[PDB]
Amino acid sequence: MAEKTVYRVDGLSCTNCAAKFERNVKEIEGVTEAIVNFGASKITVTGEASIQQVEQAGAFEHLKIIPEKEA
């Protein structure tokens, strides 16, 4: 279809880690865009990927990212 999704992330609070994270996502080939609102919010992925890969990437700090599944 056009797989944009946004998931909540929690634990961390560092811009450098935000930067490293969005970059980590961008360096995955399955995604097209991603917008990481780290601090106390959420991570948008857009392309044809799922948090699983981003989550794996986040093993650097062991983030937990929960799908903000509406309904």
Image (cartoon, helix red, strand yellow):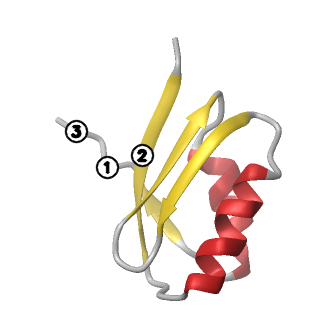
Q: Amino acid at mark 2?
A: Val
For the residues labelled 3 and 2, the Cα–Cα distance comes to 10 Å
Of the image marks 2 and 1, the number of the one nearer the N terminus:
2
Q: Residues within 10 Å of mark 2 (few under 14, many from 20)?
A: many
Residue to which mark 2 is pinned: 6
Which residue is located at x 31 percent, y 49 percent? 68
Residue to which mark 1 is pinned: 68
- Viewer-nearest of labels 2 and 1? 2
Label 2 SS: strand
For the residues labelled 3 and 1, the Cα–Cα distance comes to 6 Å
Q: Quadrant of residue 62?
A: bottom right
Residue to which mark 3 is pinned: 70
x then y, percent, for residue 37: 44, 65
User: CB of mark 3 within 8 Å of CB of mark 1?
Assistant: yes
- Viewer-nearest of labels 3 and 2? 2
Q: Is residue 35 visible?
A: yes
Tell me the quadrant of the picture where the C terminus can be found. Answer: top left
Q: Amino acid at mark 3?
A: Glu
Q: Residues within 10 Å of mark 1 (few under 14, many from 20)?
A: few
For the residues labelled 2 and 1, the Cα–Cα distance comes to 7 Å
